[PDB]
Length: 169
Ligand SMILES: Cc1cc2nc3c(=O)[nH]c(=O)nc-3n(C[C@H](O)[C@H](O)[C@H](O)COP(=O)(O)O)c2cc1C
Image 1 (cartoon, rainbow, N blue to C red):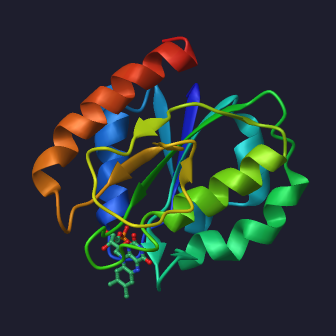
Image 2 (tube, helix red, strand yellow; image 1 turned 120 degrees about the vertical axis):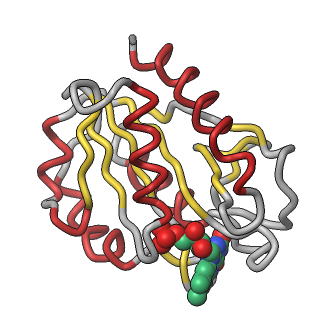
């Protein structure tokens, strides 16, 4: 497909979100779903449009599967690629490390020459600190199933609608 979605997940929440995003875009013919646990860094090279999903774990850390491939990311040339990010987190329980994984990955991938698209407003959340915030916006979609599951469906619909414009759909 045109868009490659790569996600990592520990308790399955990020996978469910990935599946909803693929569905909102139009299905398998538009978005390829890939579990980063089963991929090689070079698989990211096959796409010009990428969506990266990762939940934050263990107080500000990357989900372990993303942690595993992190050092290999240097071998991929992201210049010219448009990359969007999404993450699952818990704003109440980890108010000072909310969605940090998403920010760690964005800082790394953009330093390799990619363009970040998909900024999201921070006003619909209550947290103290997040490494995924730059100039008062999140660098990608923040989902919180632990505290705001009622908002997930419309957050995804709205985000995907905005991304379509960025990805030329
Ligand atoms: C042990 C543990 C640590 C967590 N640490 C963080 C954290 O530092 N920041 C955050 O935003 N959420 C944190 N969370 C919340 C998870 O990211 C959240 O539950 C998410 O839905 C997990 O998605 P997964 O099922 O895709 O792995 C933590 C949850 C647990 C159980």
